[PDB]
Image (cartoon, rainbow, N blue to C red):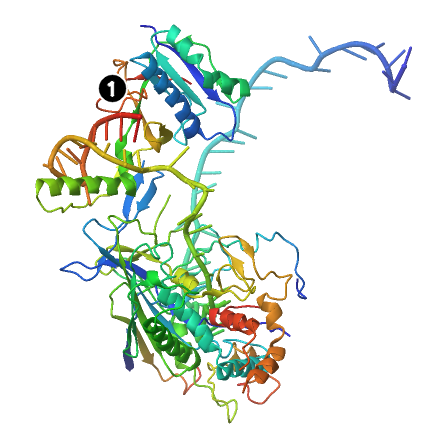
Amino acid sequence: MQRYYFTVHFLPKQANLALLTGRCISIMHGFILKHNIEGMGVTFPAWSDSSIGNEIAFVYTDKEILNTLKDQAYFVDMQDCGFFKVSQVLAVPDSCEEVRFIRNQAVAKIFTGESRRRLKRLQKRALARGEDFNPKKIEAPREIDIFHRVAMTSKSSQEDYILHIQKQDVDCQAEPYFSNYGLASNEKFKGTVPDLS
Amino acid sequence: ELCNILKYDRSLYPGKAVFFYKTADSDFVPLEADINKIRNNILTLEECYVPPNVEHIFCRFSLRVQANSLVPSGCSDPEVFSLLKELAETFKECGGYKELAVRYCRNILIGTWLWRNQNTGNTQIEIKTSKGSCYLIDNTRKLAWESKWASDDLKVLEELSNEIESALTDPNVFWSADITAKIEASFCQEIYPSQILNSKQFVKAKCADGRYAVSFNSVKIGAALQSIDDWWDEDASKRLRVHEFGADKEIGVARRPPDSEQNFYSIFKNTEWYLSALKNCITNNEKIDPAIYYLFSVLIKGGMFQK
Amino acid sequence: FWSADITAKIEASFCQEIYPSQILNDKVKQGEASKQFVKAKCADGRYAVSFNSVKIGAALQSIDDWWDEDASKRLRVHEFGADKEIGVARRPPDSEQNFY
Amino acid sequence: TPQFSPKNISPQDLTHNNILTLEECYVPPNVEHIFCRFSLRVQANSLVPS
RNA sequence: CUGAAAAUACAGUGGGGCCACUAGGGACAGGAUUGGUGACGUGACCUGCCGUAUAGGCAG
């Protein structure tokens, strides 16, 4: 029940945060798929409106498996090189302070490529059904709240893409149900993580 | 030698180049950007692409030409004024304005002025002149500076260069041209108009009905037409936009530096020398010195130069 | 009591540049534009781009070609016949041709 | 320099730009005619000094 | 190893009463700011699925 966590702090000032945040989440994703783990959450302690911070923290109920994830190759290698500061497995202060980091896919619609892909599909489907393809445009400009980028590579398809992460604040803890990037996708998954500083 | 208040007015007046497409009902539907705002210190991200059912897109602009490169607009020294006047007259009568006019005209025909949208599809260019001529290029994608053209495109080049040269030399002739490019667009092709410096916003032209159509700055189309300067060295890799120090924007260093004798002012100090060279070049198969072509290309650019 | 209403109608080219009166800015802050245009504020609240009255006045009184018997150029009527193009006074105070 | 000699500052700084904040007036697209109107009053003020 | 050493200024306190700045008044004549200018191509925002849907949700 007592949710333990550790924290990876990025020491260099000239570090591309979207890259390193992606690497840490990808290694967690790989580990989760290998070991068949469910309930793993990701939190950004040093989250600003300017940017995501130098810190990324992994929140789970078991202590041994977090200790196993702390003892992965990349973490100890980048700690030996002196770029990473990896914290020990500490119990959460467990007072309150729950937030929810969501991967909002709707952010992807502000770019031209998405509209081109989406219209190509609608054309094929409208043509398949047998009607004329005539989509109608929006009158209001698209309203989005601040989001931060996490650069992610598909090793299956060798495709570079980006996770559009948005932070929401909730009152009290919900059930630990997340995506395979531990990232509570705002309808399917409703998983909360403790706010750290 | 050089005066206090020497200044020239530019000779080529291009307008704003508007992007649009033609439907069954309307023959001017403005191409609108998609505004997205974020967050109140709101950031505005704008993207521009061809609407799904549209198969051709049009870039249109007007070019009017005055003969504002014969005498300076202002001058303190009378002898300089008389010298430049006689130099211009000498250069005109020798027939160098023809060579400048051809280079200016060729850039119009190969669609340089379509900057990042050039040869993305099968572009055709229509040119309607004030004198009731109508030229058509048919395929922009089959032309190039160094390439040898078909007789049709060379006839178009000859005729339009003659009209531009006459406009550049005669003060009593008012000359304009309406230039449209029709590009075969792919499915939701991304379009690259001019951006604002200050987030990402596009240079818009507000129509009469209130809608904003993405476009190029006049200065940018100008910069395309006046991209002829390859005289700086014998084997020049590119053609520079005409600059007084031969400044290359992409690479970011001057090709006619102030230390050298090929910058504008060093050549402008030898006018009485080049006049005698041009007077010898009259009656004579002898070619004109490229320094004078660079000189007159700067005078066709204009400036409020020294000082 | 005589008054005229004078209107010019120019057959404009496609997105042709217009050249109205420019407001001086030697005292320049880098926030707002340096080169501005003289504007006539309408009753609706919009700003119509315009010429100064003195600018129009300077054009009508460009009639002075009496400063030489073979001078074709007409100066704006000045007490010293100032020509700001070539940058000399065509009626200098040394001469008998100045107003005074 | 004032007497025509090149002072030595960076070769890359010569191709460098200046940011200009201007106001621009263009005719809206597909507007055939523009109009300029002023009113002129004439008074007999040159007969007698004020 | 100093114009040398050493040093408790203290207790108490009623500024009050009265008050008319007023009269008079032309800033005015004249005015050309003007010439000349390329925001981006060492970049993450991709490729697909569900859905009647440029709605809205999703997989690497």
Name the residue at the bottom extreme.
C69
Vertical comparison of E36 with C57: above or below: above
Q: Residue B127's x, y, as percent?
A: 30, 70
Identified at 37% across, 18% down, the residue is A28
Look at label 1 and name its amino acid: Lys
Q: Nearer the viewer, residue C72 or B110?
A: B110
Q: Is residue B198 visible?
A: no
Q: Residue at x 37, y 51 (%)?
A: B195
Please tell me which residue is depicted at 57% across the width and 56% down the height of the picture. Answer: D14
The quarter of the picture where the N terminus of chain B appears is bottom right
- The residue shown at (36%, 29%) is A152
Q: Is residue C24 above or below residue B153?
A: above
Task: Judge by depth and name the residue closer to the eye, A26 or C39.
Answer: A26
In the displayed structure, would residue C42 be above or below residue A48? below
Q: Residues within 10 Å of mark 1 (few under 14, many from 20)?
A: some
**Where does the image place residue B145, in percent across and percent down from the top left?**
42, 65
Q: How many marks?
A: 1
Note whether B278 is above or below C66 in the view shown: above
Q: Is residue D8 left or right of residue A106?
A: right
Name the spot of residue E49 as percent of width and height, x first: 19, 31
Q: Which residue is mark 1?
A: A190
Q: Where residue A143 appears, x then y in whole percent?
A: 26, 38
Badge 1: chain ID: A
